[PDB]
Amino acid sequence: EVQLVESGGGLVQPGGSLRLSCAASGFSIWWSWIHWVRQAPGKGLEWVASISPSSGWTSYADSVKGRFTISADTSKNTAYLQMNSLRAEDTAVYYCARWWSSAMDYWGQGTLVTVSSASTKGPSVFPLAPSSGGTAALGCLVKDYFPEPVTVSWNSGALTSGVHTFPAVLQSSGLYSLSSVVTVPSSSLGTQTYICNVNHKPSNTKVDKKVEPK
Amino acid sequence: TQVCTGTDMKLRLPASPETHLDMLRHLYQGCQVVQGNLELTYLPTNASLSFLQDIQEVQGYVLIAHNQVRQVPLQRLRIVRGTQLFEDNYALAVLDNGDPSPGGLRELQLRSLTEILKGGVLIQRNPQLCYQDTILWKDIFHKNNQLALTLIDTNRSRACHPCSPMCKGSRCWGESSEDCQSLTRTVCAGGCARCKGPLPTDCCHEQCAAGCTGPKHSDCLACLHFNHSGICELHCPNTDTFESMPNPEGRYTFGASCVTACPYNYLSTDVGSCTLVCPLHNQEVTAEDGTQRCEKCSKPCARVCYGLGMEHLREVRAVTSANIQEFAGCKKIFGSLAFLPESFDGDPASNTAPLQPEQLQVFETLEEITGYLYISAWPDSLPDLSVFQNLQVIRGRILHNGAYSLTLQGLGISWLGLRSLRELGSGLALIHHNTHLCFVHTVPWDQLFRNPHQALLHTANRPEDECVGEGLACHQLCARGHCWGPGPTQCVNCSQFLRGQECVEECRVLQGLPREYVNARHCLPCHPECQPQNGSVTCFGPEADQCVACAHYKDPPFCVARCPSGVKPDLSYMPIWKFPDEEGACQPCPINCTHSCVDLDDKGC
Amino acid sequence: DIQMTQSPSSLSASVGDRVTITCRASQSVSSAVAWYQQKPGKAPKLLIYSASSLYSGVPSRFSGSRSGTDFTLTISSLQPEDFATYYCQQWWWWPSTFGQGTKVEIKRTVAAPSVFIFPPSDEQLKSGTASVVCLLNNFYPREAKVQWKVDNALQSGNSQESVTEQDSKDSTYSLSSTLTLSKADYEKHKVYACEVTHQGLSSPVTKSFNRGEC
Ligand SMILES: *[C@@H]1O[C@H](CO[C@@H]2O[C@@H](C)[C@@H](O)[C@@H](O)[C@@H]2O)[C@@H](O[C@@H]2O[C@H](CO)[C@@H](O[C@@H]3O[C@H](CO)[C@@H](O)[C@H](O)[C@@H]3O)[C@H](O)[C@H]2NC(C)=O)[C@H](O)[C@H]1NC(C)=O
Ligand SMILES: *[C@@H]1O[C@H](CO)[C@@H](O[C@@H]2O[C@H](CO)[C@@H](O[C@@H]3O[C@H](CO)[C@@H](O)[C@H](O)[C@@H]3O)[C@H](O)[C@H]2NC(C)=O)[C@H](O)[C@H]1NC(C)=O
Ligand SMILES: [Cl-]
């Protein structure tokens, strides 16, 4: 019931700024002790900043001091991270967490901040159809988008097992591309079709491409 | 000071045995009259107890129990009054001293005790104790029926030496020659409640207790009722006679003495007494001195927040989710606050949910507690006691365990954050076993206490030498190195200037975001219509008439955004129409209407 | 500052094994240590706090012990879903600091991949670029070898691979290979084949399709 739902990530140009929200339910942020933690792609966890809003104590890592402002609005029950003068090495997945005992018990889902000069590109989704077994595979191809991430689910989250969504690959063009497959009985083709739900938030694209045996 | 509080912990095992004796020591060092119960319990063998040596008089009961120490030096104790009794029957209770070279109380040595006014004596299970059976208790008692409430066990693990050869008739409090029992009642002439000898001329004044040195009411060893500056009297001072004599006016009855004015933390009554609690139909007004007084309500008495040990919560032992809402919006609680493990775990026997952390918000308005604050459990989410951010005084008129006005134990908060706390009226503070807690020794307790007989007792918190880095010691900008927690928002006193809650190096007087003036070490914003000045003062106050120069137009004497256009400063005043200069000063319009005027004039009036 | 150092960097263990992970504080850090479990691309999950105590809902397998400055997260018998990176964290000194992490990988028996071949979508053909997808489904160990054949011509430097994170039930990987070709070089050819070499394969698997002809 105690939850942290954070938002505000996405794409920013170098030198530009961005603000991250961390909305709480199940507890008061004001009396609590909120911490921000980042994780550059393929790296360890790194502490960034913290706030005890009631006491007024705000703390920052030498890495981000003077660029970042931590704050909290009590009425909204939300903690914020204002990030200014962003650079390449700020590109990471930022988490917010709640201090407890002497650890962080409740964490946010983590939002992705990507600092790049390239502009936002929407993905085009292409079907991967089975041919003429016992068990056969089908899926979608989410090609040419920027930046990360893309969310692929099947039949509005109703179909889960058999599903493999591959981690995206950086292409020569600088754009991303991934594939998402699923295996199903070879006697289900025709009278049972499946819909993949592609969602690229930065570009506002919600494609529902139904894959059919052809 | 000579008058001190007692304790009220009975046979309960000490909450921190490490600093239990230190409690006793601070409490009784120099004390002569114990306004309550003298409880000397759980004292280890080597225990240094010389701080008791001035106790002369006890109001409540004397309870000497569960000690391994061989003697308690209470030689100057003359009288126990028994205003309160142990187990509702006993004025002196000496219980379980020594296990069932060897430990245990050997002698009582109450060589001066000659009056127990109320209740009996209970002496039991003291394997090393000698001579208690020797004492003629009847003499010490005020009335004979007090004998009927006396039980004196003589089971013993050792042979006793005889009383000193110099002892009257084999009655003593110990092996010493000055340990003989002095009889002041059963040995008397004629009437006489107390005598200094067996002749009629050896009677003590009607108003003495314990005995005397002569016949006058100034020769008393103790006052039976009240001590009026060295004269024992039946009453504290409606005149019948046409004259005036010495001995100052009228007095307040405080304990068993008449005094000029009530002591520091007490309350004077219309009935002419000092108290720690007002009667019904009564408020509590603070004089310009800081003096408190109970007085009848002229209207019906207004709403009052009662804490624990008061009104409907007099039996309730802790703040739970059942009564947390009762403190909503309270600026001043009349009673105490206690947070126990059972507060946040929640008793599953009664349908009482565990109290949630954000429910402690109710206490955000709180400024004053008359009783005590006790915290033995706190939510693991909360790093500090910031919900008590605004608490200014804890009077301690009611003390937890009869001794402590502020107790913080077993918490695992990292800092305190009680940043408005300026006064602990009376009692000791105890902060122990908070393994994570720093900023305990960065607080100037010397300034929170009032009398110099109170102190902080601390043990098993985070080591002092381990509170050193950032987030662990006071901020640079805190004055005199005093703070309630980390950062420039936790200073006790501010080294330079305050911008709201924060300690800052400089106000934006000459340079900065929005310009500021200083007022009483406070950074405060200039009016938006002030024009920022190059390396010079921008404004002198918050009002738009206090700018050095205007950012836009000026409308004497104000710096304005635009010149008045048909505004009326109030009703019945005709509207004021103006236009700007080439310079920027707002100028009045000419002849009324047709050309209603503005810069180059407009119709429609 | 203060340094948390974990050992080993990575470890591989079979299901049921007694895994232990060391974390070493540079100075005395008291009992104030926490252990986290982070699955790839999700929030860290708290396991142990205050060195010894384990958080609610955490299975009996996870335990923590302290000896001086040497802290030991230890899993009594490893389970297939325990694949993650594990981080220790200290709380005694400020700022709080993390260990560099320990990646724990699951060892299992050799499993042959299920191979599938997907033809470039009809919709995508009306764009001027074609993507040919090859799927290696549910296999172990990781190192496979995919090779593309366009009319029996071995392709080079024009395809990219992506590996699934180890499945939390049967600990198998999945692989996707993608052949990116222009419409021109795709319409010049007819028979498209994907060639797979794995330890579970006695001989290479090949899956084909005949462009618009069957
Ligand atoms: C002097 O002490 C004796 C007991 O002798 C010993 O020292 C004590 C301090 C304890 O440590 C004892 O365990 C030890 O034996 C006291 O005698 C006891 O008195 C009680 C009544 O007060 C007798 O009642 C008994 O109670 C038990 C348990 O409830 C029942 O099983 C019995 O049926 C019986 O009713 C008891 O018999 C008696 N103990 C002995 C040894 O028989 C004595 O009270 C004490 N004197 C004074 C003045 O306090
Ligand atoms: C009744 O109460 C009065 C208080 O008005 C007591 O008189 C005070 O008692 C002290 C000690 O007996 C007297 O002597 C003085 O003591 C102080 C402190 O020890 C010492 O510094 C002085 O040199 C002096 O010897 C003094 O008369 C008086 N003290 C003061 C300051 O008021 C009286 O003791 C009490 N009597 C009974 C019957 O209990
Ligand atoms: Cl002793």
Image (spheres, rainbow, N blue to C red):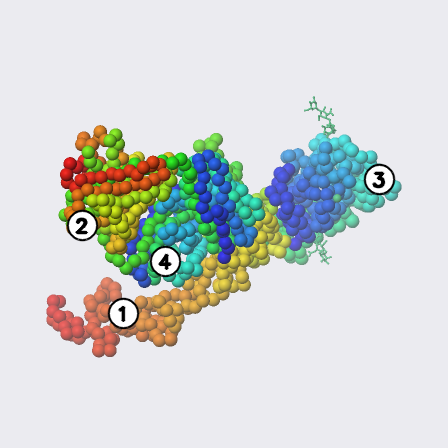
Q: Amino acid at mark 2?
A: Asp
> On screen, B569 above or below C57?
below
Q: Secondary structure at mark 2?
A: helix
Identify residue for label 4. A89
Residue under the image location 30 percent in, 44 percent down: C146
Q: Are marks 4 and 2 on the same chain?
A: no
Q: Secondary structure at mark 1?
A: strand
Chain identity of mark 2: C
Residue under the image location 72 percent in, 35 percent down: B99
Residue under the image location 23 percent in, 50 percent down: A144
Neighbor class of circle 2 (other Cα within 10 Å; few <14, some 14-19, many 20+) is: few
Neighbor class of circle 4 (other Cα within 10 Å; few <14, some 14-19, many 20+) is: few
Identify residue for label 2. C185
Q: Position of residue B561 (x, y in %)?
A: 25, 68
Residue lying furthest right: B165
Q: How many marks?
A: 4
Which is closer to the viewer, label 4 or label 2?
2
Residue under the image location 26 percent in, 58 percent down: A118
Which is closer to the viewer, label 1 or label 4?
4
Q: Tell me if I can see residue B287 in this picture.
A: no
Identify residue for label 1. B560
Q: Tell me if I can see residue C75 in this picture.
A: yes
Neighbor class of circle 3 (other Cα within 10 Å; few <14, some 14-19, many 20+) is: many
Label 3 – label 1 distance at C-alpha: 98 Å
Neighbor class of circle 1 (other Cα within 10 Å; few <14, some 14-19, many 20+) is: many
Q: Amino acid at mark 1?
A: Val
Chain identity of mark 4: A
Q: Quadrant of residue B145?
A: top right
